[PDB]
Image: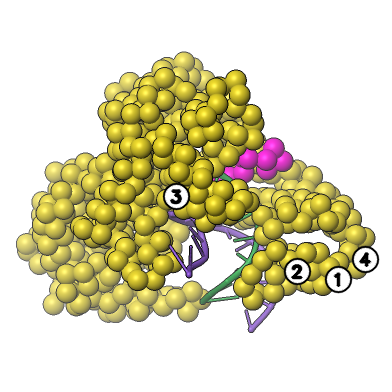
Chain colours: A yellow, B green, C purple
DNA sequence: GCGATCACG
DNA sequence: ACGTACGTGATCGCA
């Protein structure tokens, strides 16, 4: 039972409560709050938001850091409230982040899924209540109120068991000192948004519609026929049946036309280079011009991403609607998209700071590999040094092709090395790749010992860990299926590296936000892209940021090798290079 | 809805 | 003998 309240009472404002501030729309930016539930020592309450959020005592309670709240996905509530000019403080327990740290593979995305981890089933999945996709809707008040009170009651009854298990895992500080403070910082970043130069985007797309038409007509002429270049089935028929190009592959999905296949097919027909170019331009038009403009707010011309903090299996963030972690940079034609990402105020600039080789520096630290540690203590070009070691040549004798192949070896080492995977990447034989790998481990025997030991540890304990005690369970490590077991072995090798790098930049974000506040700088974090942080600030703060941001990022943790941070700034994101 | 594809670190 | 590089999200075509 619970109270369907018509007005806020003092009983509802106790100094510890489970709080539900329900936002049903997936994108919570400027979205409605459909209902509120409070569970505390005095009872269970459902409040209508138009009543509660207009009540000064309830708003003061929400903003009082000394009034502690337990929630699920507090960032969603905090951001929805920010759009209403209401501050949420005092969130001491977030069940979504607790569940994520205990086991990221559960895919916990609602209270019911977290509750099932502790045999609590007296709450419905959100999808059962609201529906999926187009059939989605807020139910009538009796159904909605019971659901919100059941979620608040579940949070109330799950905080202790979840904290107990986090404690046993030595993850309690990871929740309270890393993920929960980070959630508030991410909320600020998403709410600030990034300003988009939409007229430049519209022009850029224009440059693109003309070039697409040009290459599309060239492809039709070369194919001797007009067809749907973007259809995988149709392209494969044109290439491999009409034009009779060679098929170097498997499976029975018609034919693969991925860029790695087309790059090998290019010497056989002029059409292949044009299809690759058409693919590049069409990706920019559909995803990064048209798709971006769809989610720009028409009034402010800002995009407000949502950073999913409880999704990836390694501890990284992800970014949605739009994804601001995969904006084009590698080819110049795509890189120009970043000219459309601009500071949100006049006379401000974009400032970008990135870790240099954080994953291999983490590997040097965790493996305690003498040669790799010394390479970073000398601040060597790690791919040139790896080439020197594996091909047994002096620095002057490293050719560009040697550095390229050594770089691919380094990628494989971080991903979880295999002769098959390296051979596929470098387009060489498994035996040739195995020789590269053997040479690598002769030069980096500590890395070899580390990789052997971490796979054995994953088998023994059932999971692997990161520097700050994030965990990933790997039950497939004991599979008698070669493919299944090999997947788990690569995850055992990769997750402590990628995940520790994620831990470090998350701590850097917390440290940076604190330093920006101490210095009373106007600079603000806008984005994180795995190993880099993107800020905007007044032009008059650039000199201070050039010293502050790299130092904070470099000092976030202390490893057996230095951390190194590069930085750039300019008038647009493109120019911060 | 799902696989293929390609964008990023 | 075995055959996938690690981690993500958006779009498209097609069933
Ligand atoms: Mg970098």
Answer yes or no: are tags 3 and 4 on the same subunit: yes
Q: Which residue is mark 3?
A: A417
Magenta region includes residue A321: yes
Q: Which of A456 and A532 lies nearest the eye of the viewer?
A: A456
Magenta region includes residue A429: no
- Count of all numbered marks drawn on residues in the image: 4
Query: Residue A263, relative to residue A64: is it above or below?
Result: below
Q: Which chain is mark 4 on?
A: A
Give the residue displayed 66% in from the left and 66% down from the top: A249
**Is label 1 in contact with label 3 (beta carbons under 8 Å)?**
no
Q: Which chain is mark 3 on?
A: A
Query: Residue A440, relative to residue A536: is it above or below?
Result: below
Q: Which residue is mark 1?
A: A242
| Residue A214 pos. (x, y %) | 87, 52
Mark 1 → mark 2, Cα distance in angstroms: 9 Å
| Residue A547 pos. (x, y %) | 41, 17
**Is label 1 in contact with label 2 (beta carbons under 8 Å)?**
no
């Amino acid at each position: 039972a619970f109270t369907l309240a018509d007005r806020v009472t003092e009983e509802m404002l106790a100094d510890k409560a489970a709080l539900v501030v329900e936002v049903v729309e997936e994108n919570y930016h400027d979205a409605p709050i459909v209902g509120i539930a409070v569970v505390n020592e005095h009872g269970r309450f459902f409040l209508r938001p138009e009543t509660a959020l207009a009540d000064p005592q309830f708003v003061a309670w929400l903003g009082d850091e000394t009034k502690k709240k337990s929630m699920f996905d507090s960032k969603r509530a905090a951001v929805a409230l920010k759009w209403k000019g209401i501050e949420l403080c005092g969130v001491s327990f977030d069940l979504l982040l607790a569940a994520y740290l205990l086991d990221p593979a559960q895919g916990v995305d609602d209270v019911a899924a977290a509750a099932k981890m502790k045999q609590y089933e007296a709450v419905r999945p959100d999808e059962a209540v609201y529906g999926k996709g187009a059939k989605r809707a807020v139910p009538d008040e009796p159904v909605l109120a019971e659901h919100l009170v059941r979620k608040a009651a579940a949070i109330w009854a799950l905080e202790r068991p979840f904290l107990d298990e986090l404690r046993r895992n030595e993850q309690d500080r990871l929740l309270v000192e890393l993920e929960q403070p980070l959630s508030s910082i991410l909320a600020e970043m998403e709410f600030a948004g990034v300003k988009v130069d939409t007229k430049r985007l519209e022009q850029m797309g224009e440059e693109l519609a003309e070039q697409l038409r040009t290459v599309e007509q060239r492809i039709y002429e070369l194919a001797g026929q007009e067809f749907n270049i973007n259809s995988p089935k149709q392209l494969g028929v044109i290439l491999f049946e009409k034009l009779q190009l060679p098929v170097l592959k498997k499976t029975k999905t018609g034919y693969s036309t991925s860029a790695d296949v087309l790059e090998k097919l290019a010497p056989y027909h002029e059409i292949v280079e044009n299809i690759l170019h058409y693919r590049q331009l069409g990706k920019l038009q559909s995803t990064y011009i048209e798709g971006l403009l769809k989610v720009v707010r028409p009034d402010t011309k800002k995009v407000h991403t949502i950073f999913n903090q409880a999704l990836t299996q390694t501890g990284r963030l992800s970014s949605t609607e739009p994804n601001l972690q995969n904006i084009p940079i590698r080819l110049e034609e795509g890189r120009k998209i970043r000219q459309a990402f601009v500071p949100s105020e006049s006379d401000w600039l974009i400032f970008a700071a990135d870790y240099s080789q954080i994953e291999l520096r983490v590997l040097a630290h965790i493996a305690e590999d003498d040669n790799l540690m010394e390479a970073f203590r000398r601040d060597l070009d790690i791919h040139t040094k790896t080439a020197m070691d594996i091909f047994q040549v002096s620095e002057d004798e490293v050719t560009p092709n040697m550095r390229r192949q050594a770089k691919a070896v380094n990628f494989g080492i971080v991903y979880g090395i295999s002769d098959y995977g390296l051979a596929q990447n470098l387009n060489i034989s498994r035996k040739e790749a195995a020789e590269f790998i053997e040479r690598y481990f002769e030069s980096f025997p500590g890395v070899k010992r580390y990789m052997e030991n971490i796979v054995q540890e994953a088998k023994q304990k059932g999971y692997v860990t990161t520097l700050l005690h994030r965990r990933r369970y790997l039950p497939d490590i004991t599979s008698r299926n070669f493919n299944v077991r090999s997947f788990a072995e690569r995850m055992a090798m990769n997750t402590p590296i990628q995940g520790s790098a994620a831990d470090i930049i998350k701590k850097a974000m917390i440290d940076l936000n604190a330093r920006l506040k101490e210095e009373r700088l106007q600079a603000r974090l806008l984005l994180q892209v795995h190993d880099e942080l993107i800020l905007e600030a007044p032009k008059e703060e650039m000199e201070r940021l050039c010293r502050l941001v790299p130092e904070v990022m470099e000092q976030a943790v202390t490893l057996r090798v230095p951390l190194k941070v590069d930085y750039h700034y300019g008038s647009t994101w493109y120019d911060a290079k």
